[PDB]
Length: 50
Length: 49
Length: 50
Image 1 (cartoon, each protein chain N blue to C red):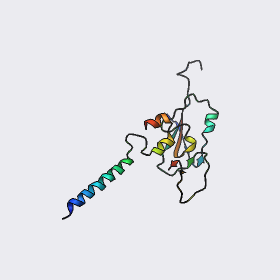
Image 2: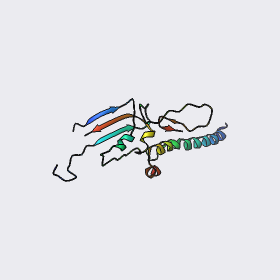
Image 3: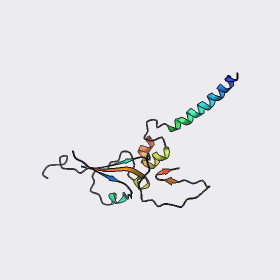
Image 4: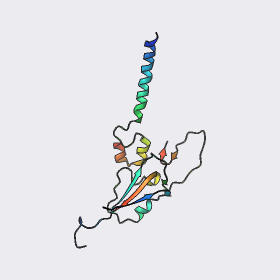
């Protein structure tokens, strides 16, 4: 009900480490490829945790 | 006076413009740019887009 | 803890992005290359390839 939202901005993101150590049974992406995240630039990045 | 000839010229230009305009249409896909689709998706779903 | 799978607590994190509609502040690890003028090149500017 009170899910935490964190803004991510002004950083360079290495998504490779998320793969390198992972306890995540489900890693499902809808609008972007998982392997292509390293080659792209983004804004309006938000992480919602619950 | 010379409306008929100009009209023909207008139609041809208009047709080309419309065809050019059609490149900016998503057509039910995530993006209208092929390069973005290749850069953002894996081949099984990129093929669909 | 005694319950089986499907009722156990699961932590979910949702990453939300926007695609190319604003200036980007979050980018991948890819290294910047020098700029070349008056030649046909395949360029990647902020995840936009042309």
